[PDB]
Length: 49
DNA sequence: AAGATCTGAATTTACGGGCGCAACTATGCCGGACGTAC
View 1 (cartoon, rainbow, N blue to C red):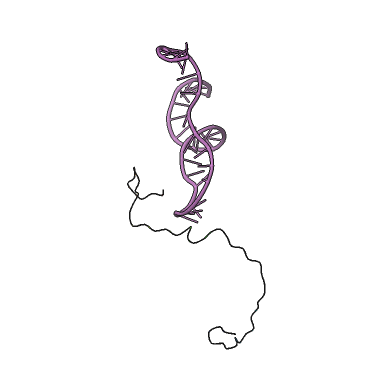
View 2 (view 1 turned 180 degrees about the vertical axis):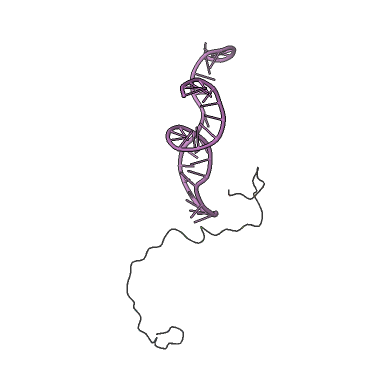
């Protein structure tokens, strides 16, 4: 049944238990942004550190 | 004619390159020589 309108969904859905795994790659560990900050000492360009 | 030379044309080593970026980790350069204290 459609959770919003409560109407029956026309086609019948394949549903059941399944084993799922959460992988270690969270979004908070891979989100970053820069405006300006720690440039290099030699190239005078942005660097990771 | 013969040759030696000799000068342009077939075969062997030898550098030098070898995906975009992300992310994370973990590891790194002494031995004699001279003094001082006990």
